[PDB]
Length: 77
Length: 204
Image 1 (cartoon, each protein chain N blue to C red):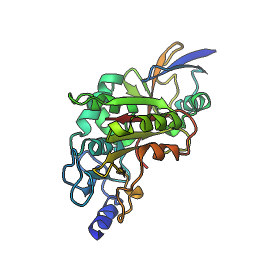
Image 2 (image 1 turned 45 degrees about the vertical axis):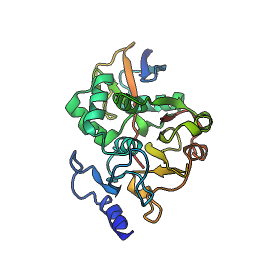
Image 3 (image 1 turned 30 degrees about the horizontal axis):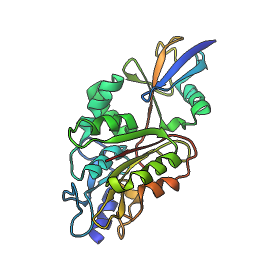
Image 4 (image 1 turned 90 degrees about the horizontal axis):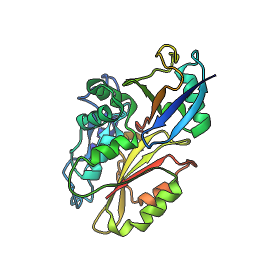
């Protein structure tokens, strides 16, 4: 199984077990199970581009051992 | 006090598409308050359009007491730290807001009085910090996040009476008869619903 890494700007890193067909929406659900951050507060960035929930890791050419930046989404409310 | 009530209604009108030129809807108090508040007791206070995700910039200005920060500062910070394109990042902040480390980076550009940040901490330990340093500070930015939060930035400001005032830019959470309520940032944090460690503070 493929393993990706998600790294926050604070320096904390988590390893996720994912697959190429997984949607970004599915990855955010895995980050919620491990860090408790609701998916609506999550920004994932790879290669200087913010990822979209509808597409898959394969659509962005994210490969195992690739690292994703997790950035919180604090708008207002 | 009705002029403020109608200004709050204005910030609810999302008819026109959001843009770099209309995300700021108005002001509760438009005059500068770098130190003390005005004669009406109010600090500089911006009102954001409801659909804008720019709470961080408006709170940062309440933190400073003037219109010191705009989209250029936060976009430049996001481009430098995560590699986003600068023009893109300006549109993305309108949509997706600002992470606590971006805010930290923006406030520390201003050389002079230092800003102390504590990021990714529980509310209980941040409140204890705010109680420990209370006498030595007069302004705070509170980033809210985690389960039970919508994701929001609030500013706090201390007056000559040594009373704290909550300055919230989201127009749904402003009451025209008391737009800057009396509440300490420490107690504000102690009453948050979230239970994990995704809160953040920046004080001076």
